[PDB]
View 1 (cartoon, rainbow, N blue to C red):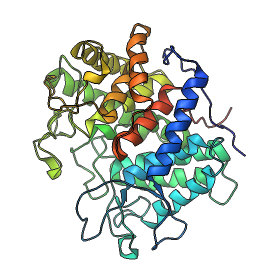
View 2: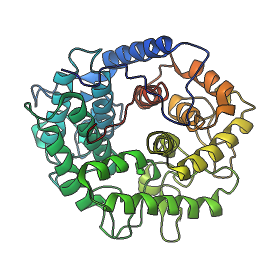
View 3: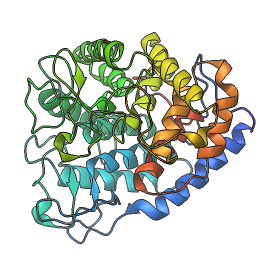
View 4: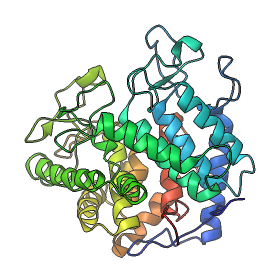
Length: 387
């Protein structure tokens, strides 16, 4: 009953795939990576929610006295991965519906159309936590994929669930009056605080195509404006953006923003995800502003590393100075993805593929590496409202 079974192995206009191996090799690498990811991270052991699934994060410490097991961010990653692997994993729909059960049971304490950001094995946690924008973005987008994979005439009306989450959830709570995306449903409607890894341009395009609400296009265009307004001043040579961005005109967040890290003003663990989220817009929708941003970052990192992906480190100041020390896939793999819009990057893309295809480390890097591998092999297909 899959209408888009793995592997869809699509060919987006103007983008290259790794070409030193066959497509069957690329698909086999993705299948193996998924089987290992699923074994290590996909869980269905919530005593407080039989039938609920989640993705096991690490997460040090407690969250409001609860022991955090996963987040809405990982829930969204897992839900996208699961729908895309349908046709290989015969339990994909059961897993997806179980992830959705968790997402709606652990609803946000603020906007109940969203997911609260922490999964913990307690009925008290179900409805206790507020939302985080990126988790709900990936969850809502995954519902569009589910609609196109299985149709919406079964137990879960995926399209209606998507439309409600997009409109009553994300637009209502996270689209700001300044046409940005705020940090979560606890943040204000007039907030100028934003996390650029939430600027999931290609998801926002799909939201527009499946709701017809032009708000999404207004946000896309404005966020491209913001990216350029920020980078021309703060990263004119590298093209990078910081983990968090504040104020108008946009500027790097201060250090220790939200107590996340000393490097919230820099290209750190949140922003490492940006180059994938941006490049997908060029690949799936032909957006030239995405190619411009992607080529600038790709050229910078290739020169920085002398064409060696293993020389990428886990964090950079906006001027390109090293913060990190070692190559991890949440940084490496999006830099490879950013490189796919120019054919003269072929060798670099091939080297990046060899680096990432078997690279297993921990939840955050592995989950984002799998999303990136799905995308760069053509196996993340585009949901379209019909034929």
